[PDB]
Length: 330
Ligand SMILES: Cc1c(C=O)c(-c2nnc3c4c(C[n+]5cc6c(C)n(C)c(C)c6c(Cl)n5)n(C)c(C)c4cnn23)c(C)n1C
Image 1: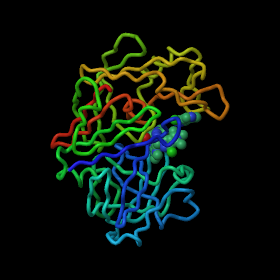
Image 2 (image 1 turned 45 degrees about the vertical axis):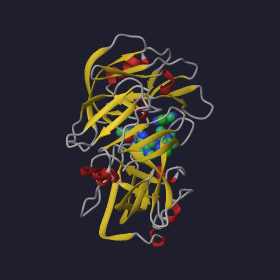
Image 3 (image 1 turned 120 degrees about the vertical axis):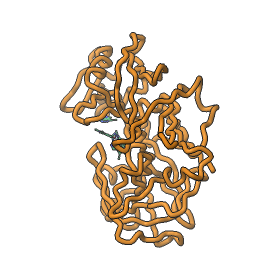
Image 4 (image 1 turned 180 degrees about the vertical axis):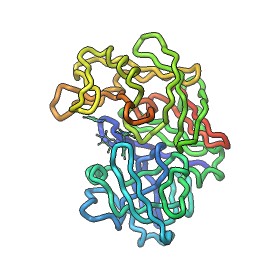
């Protein structure tokens, strides 16, 4: 089997991407944030504290003839931005782009933190990291991909995120029309539950490539690119007026700037992020100071190849017995 679904930016800055997912019988379609940095499929629901729902579409398990309460199971998660959610668990039929999993754990939120409430466009998350990170207790549950894998034509999914435009998540096949050149595959460590890999270096603009190992995670849930402070300083030093602002929370730059590109290495291959992918717009409405899309990972404890990086590539998440990642230009 295969599946193919379009993923759409939630706003004009590509702050996140939503992908429609069918849950239950008859189907209830919710728009989920596909997140290769976590492993829970959770949704706003008829159980979510009413004051914490503000415009999201909810899953109502009592209206699904295939929903079954997973007795005694609870979940609770907290994300890298400090947001969180928790609740109980059903199993139900879940379909993505024509690919169906029966008996998928659907984690129903009873509580969500303010950033979830305040974002009406995201109805939940669909985790695509390794199932070892799943938070369901006392019996850990499998991701949608893990459940689907054995049925897929090939045990892979691909992320093809757009810059200020829709893109595609495919399951079970590699669309050879979706990229240029070849796909370069690179080793993955699953020891922390992530799609963790080692980039071979970077360049800023038309500058020379610096060969240096950068260990980090391919994380579709993360908006920005988080790299070591040395690398990030070298990038922003090429932008007149750019500075790190403690009050704002990162590097900012004059909105009048023309940003240089940023290149990262995948083996001997190179992925070029155009400068405009690095512009996240005014820090507050009407400001002439703009927020940068490349930020320091100092304090995070891990480097994160988030959407800024991934949207410059066609990315293969290869879930073979030994997982690997593939990157192609496009
Ligand atoms: C260690 C880490 C992260 C790891 O991932 C991270 C991060 N970066 N984007 C996101 C996340 C997103 C994506 N996301 C970002 C958004 C931004 C920047 N803005 C203005 C809006 C309105 C957003 C929405 Cl609705 N959604 N979502 C939905 C969740 C649950 C995230 C959790 N963390 N996160 C940050 C800021 N940090 C420090």
